[PDB]
Image (cartoon, rainbow, N blue to C red):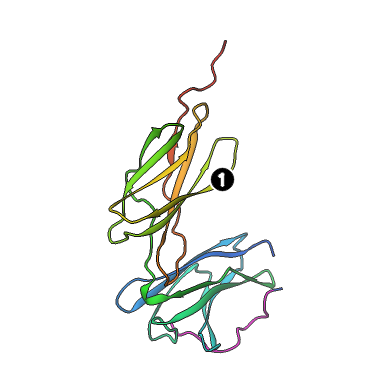
Amino acid sequence: SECCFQDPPYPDADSASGPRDLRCYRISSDRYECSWQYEGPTAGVSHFLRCCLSSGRCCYFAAGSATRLQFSDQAGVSVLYTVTLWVESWARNQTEKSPEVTLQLYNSVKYEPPLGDIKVSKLAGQLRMEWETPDNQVGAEVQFRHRTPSSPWKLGDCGPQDDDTESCLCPLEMNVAQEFQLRRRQLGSQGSSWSKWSSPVCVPPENPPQPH
């Protein structure tokens, strides 16, 4: 993969569908990976990873239908200094853009949600979740989302974390089933993107409605 420092072969975007959740990180001594998702039907859609250097020079990788792409530090993209990255999709005769991500790629780590046991218990009128920190990922911003069978996802903040274990306080609803998920973001100044959501924490109702 070489980043092509030319005008992209399509017009600029002028849509409800499109690419989103761009995550870029280093994966080895000299290789990097960007990952994203696409909202909407994927038929005939292709993706381009865009990059602008601080000098204003910009380039693109053509990814085809893939939603993930790897490149080395010889691809023309600076990794030691800050760059700006985003995804453009050619879909149904129109260009669509993701939000940008501004980061120093060399210090950007692939952060992951809790992967394994998530302990859940009651603390006063809240739920407390606790998990062991993913290896070599100490230091994180952590968010949760929660829902009930009827309600949609509502997002929340767990606060910053700095230890071998991490925790979160969440709303407790005794009379309905609850589902929670957790995601983690790298701390620091180099730039960060949210990890994927963890597997669910499922908390059945302790006082479900009863006949009288």
Instruction: Report which residue position mark 1 lands on.
Output: 154
Residue 26's place in the image compared with 185, above or below, is: below
**Of residues 51 and 184, the one drawn nearer to the viewer in this rendering:** 184
Q: Where is residue 190, by image quadrant?
A: bottom left
Q: Is residue 31 magenta?
A: no
Quadrant placement of the C terminus: top right
Residue ID at (44%, 59%) = 195
Residue ID at (68%, 69%) = 92
The amino acid type found where label 1 is placed reads Lys
- In the image, residue 170 lies at what x, y percent? 46, 41
Side (left or right) of 52 relative to 25: right
- In the image, residue 70 lies at what x, y percent? 41, 74
Residue 84's place in the image compared with 206, above or below, is: below
- In the image, residue 104 lies at what x, y percent? 42, 76
Residue 176's place in the image compared with 200, above or below, is: above
Q: Where is residue 121, by image quadrant?
A: top left
Residue ID at (31%, 53%) = 133
Q: Main secondary structure of the magenta part?
A: loop
In this rendering, the count of numbered labels is 1
Q: Where is residue 29, by image quadrant?
A: bottom left
The stretch of residues the image draws in magenta is: 1-13
Quadrant placement of the N terminus: bottom left
Neighbourhood count class around disc 1 (C-alpha, 10 Å): few under 14, some 14–19, many 20 upward:
few
Q: Residue furthest top?
A: 212
Residue ID at (52%, 89%) = 55
Q: Secondary structure at mark 1?
A: strand
Q: Is residue 12 magenta?
A: yes
Q: Residue furthest front?
A: 124
**Of residues 14 and 185, the one drawn nearer to the viewer in this rendering:** 185
- In the image, residue 66 lies at what x, y percent? 50, 69
